[PDB]
Image (spheres, coloured by chain):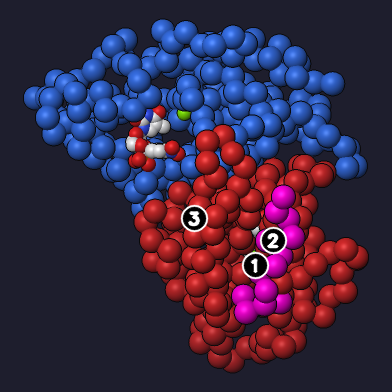
Chain colours: A blue, B red
Amino acid sequence: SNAASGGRALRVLVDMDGVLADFEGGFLRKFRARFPDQPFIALEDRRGFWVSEQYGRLRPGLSEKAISIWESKNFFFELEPLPGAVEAVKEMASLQNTDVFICTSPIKMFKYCPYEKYAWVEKYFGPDFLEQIVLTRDKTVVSADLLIDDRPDITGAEPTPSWEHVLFTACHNQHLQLQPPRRRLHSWADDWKAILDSKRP
Amino acid sequence: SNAASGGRALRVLVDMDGVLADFEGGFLRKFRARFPDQPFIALEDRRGFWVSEQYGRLRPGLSEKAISIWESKNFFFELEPLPGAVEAVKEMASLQNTDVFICTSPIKMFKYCPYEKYAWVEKYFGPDFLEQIVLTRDKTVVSADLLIDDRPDITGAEPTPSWEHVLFTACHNQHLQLQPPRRRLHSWADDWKAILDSKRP
Ligand SMILES: Cc1cn([C@H]2C[C@H]3O[C@](c4ccc([N+](=O)[O-])cc4)(P(=O)(O)O)OC[C@H]3O2)c(=O)[nH]c1=O
Ligand SMILES: Cc1cn([C@H]2C[C@H]3O[C@](c4ccc([N+](=O)[O-])cc4)(P(=O)(O)O)OC[C@H]3O2)c(=O)[nH]c1=O
Ligand SMILES: [Mg+2]
Ligand SMILES: [Mg+2]
């Protein structure tokens, strides 16, 4: 909930794909359904942020096939929420002196993805939560205390972002050793309130 | 153009409706075409940021009719650029040590508006400029040196935005007296480079 008059709430940016929405699992399911005669990458074996790059190494032309899954209509809309994600973000947004924004990057093909992200947020959080969406390819120009995001290296036009990036664990990043004092949120079952509280005055 | 390694470019946020895209003129044209037996507000007579509020005072039910224009498919996509806007922003983005983002708020009805804004940017600035779009209802959480925007009072979760708001003149705000030392950009013919240069190191 917002701070009082001209006051300062803790501001938390919550990533969408890989934090609220199960992009990796949705992708694998739809990939295997559309391309049942192609090899695929089990989630346990995922390495590196870019799915299409790993697929492109697995067999020639598979990068383009992988891309065609997330460029398809309904791919973003039909992603399942991560366990505990909707409940956690609902709770977080209800906390005193705490402003929550969903900060997400659309893919390059924009026919469906922006629309479907808004629709997904409306579905799981309600119409009033649409006010909290920030769509950007550059998260470094969004100011906050925290950014909870599964991408390991978040860069852009601002060399010194105001937020601390807490890495949200995903299949593609779970083995990564981070430079101290970078921190993780291992899942929504993990103690996200303690992370927030560490940044409060 | 971006700064060098970990370096700091001047960052300018450029609003879309009323700065790049002619929302007021597009609205009036389509309103009069769809509702030719209703009274309307000439641009010269526009007062206050919210078109639907002024229309709602003009005759009962006209607020809802006004809203139905911008909720229609193709309304955002078909807006004409303001004179000099595309040329100015192209030039600005080519300047050394200058990063330009288009920072725009979607309407509440999201079926068409986000998509059409991306499509409009692609049309006038090209595919590579899509990287520069930030869609948000709260501009105060986007950090920059300048925000060029026709809305007079830009507020949100950050009580002390990093940007200076330069008011871009529009029909609805042209008579407004601003509190010193608030500044205007009167049109894209006006000297926007001098405004940028005033914020450089
Ligand atoms: C969020 C996410 C997306 N992707 C896919 C989806 C698609 O996204 C992009 C992509 C690239 C850059 C950024 N960005 O730096 O903001 C977002 C998405 P696209 O190039 O926009 O299609 O990169 C290639 C593809 O990679 C992934 O492979 N893994 C992810 O975790
Ligand atoms: C940009 C702009 C939009 N409108 C219209 C369009 C529609 O926008 C909103 C609107 C409201 C708030 C914000 N915002 O504070 O980010 C954006 C758009 P909607 O409520 O989202 O439909 O307000 C009512 C309508 O008012 C205007 O009347 N004038 C404008 O300059
Ligand atoms: Mg992510
Ligand atoms: Mg505007």
Distance Cα–Cα, label 3 vs label 2: 32 Å
Q: CA distance from mark 1 to mark 2?
A: 6 Å
Q: Are marks 1 and 2 in contact (CB under 8 Å)?
A: yes
Label 1 neighbour load within 10 Å: few <14, some 14-19, many 20+: few
Question: Looking at the image, which residue is at 58% across and 81% down?
Answer: B25
Looking at the rendered structure, the kind of residue marked 2 is Asp
Q: Is residue B8 left or right of residue B90?
A: right
Q: Residue at x 79, y 36 (%)?
A: A2
Residue B35, given in percent of the width and then of the height, sits at 56, 85
The quarter of the rendering in which ligand 1 is drawn is top left
Q: Is residue B145 visible?
A: yes
Residue that label 1 marks: B193
The residue pinned by badge 3 equals B114
The boundaries of the magenta stretch are B186-201
Q: Position of residue B170 (x, y in %)?
A: 70, 76
Residue type of the residue flagged with mark 3: Pro
Q: Amino acid at mark 1?
A: Lys
